[PDB]
Image (tube, rainbow, N blue to C red; front, side):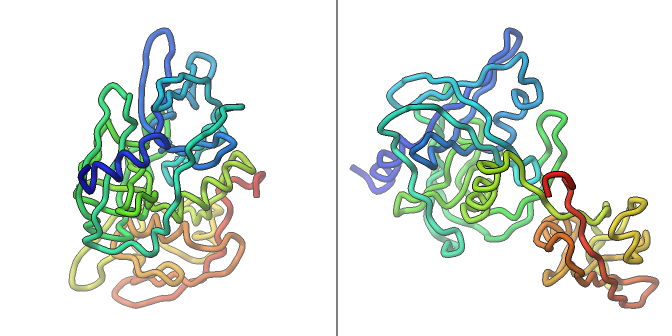
Length: 296
């Protein structure tokens, strides 16, 4: 058996098909078993339509052996494009082994593994092409668009392996394939999954700013398109046409990195925003709000 053949074969039983059907429509993706009690991780696109219209969709999980079981949505985070499902009282689950995405390096060989029985299923191979790479993702349903800090790979990521794991050569999960490919890194997945399992929700920081990217000799970064009334940004003295170049401890190259950087701030704690305003460099202070005040 070949090098990749062995790794794909070792993790196949941890990968599942997730199917959502209404009497009008029927969509399908992959996901990975992450906990022996039957917790399954996928991306938020895969279950979005069912989560938004639960009265008309039924979600099932199909195992490598072909068993089909009903699945319940535990919680989801459109901002990180992740979701968690739960199957009840299924025995002898092959739980995926979760790696450490902070140890992943550019050039590392990977498999992007889709669920073996999915209709369009794919397994692809490549390397890690970049780390900590902000990438915009369009929201599936009425879901908000977002940006994630991704693992980039030249393994093809397509309908047939999205929601499945990105697997390293130790056959460990180093990320979740999104919907020139990108994976949500496993260290972030673990933090978001933990939260969705407990609370059924994740609370992210918000400033009330929308930005557009600017690149030139005077100041490159995320130029402020809009500031929400009453927002942390309004209260902290951020102005439209300000060019944001640093948010907290993270330099901000463009509007994509701005989105990711905000989400690394502490809720309720003062933080520096560096701005270029009418040719001058200004540091403001902002106290981020929770995006969901009642779950904070």
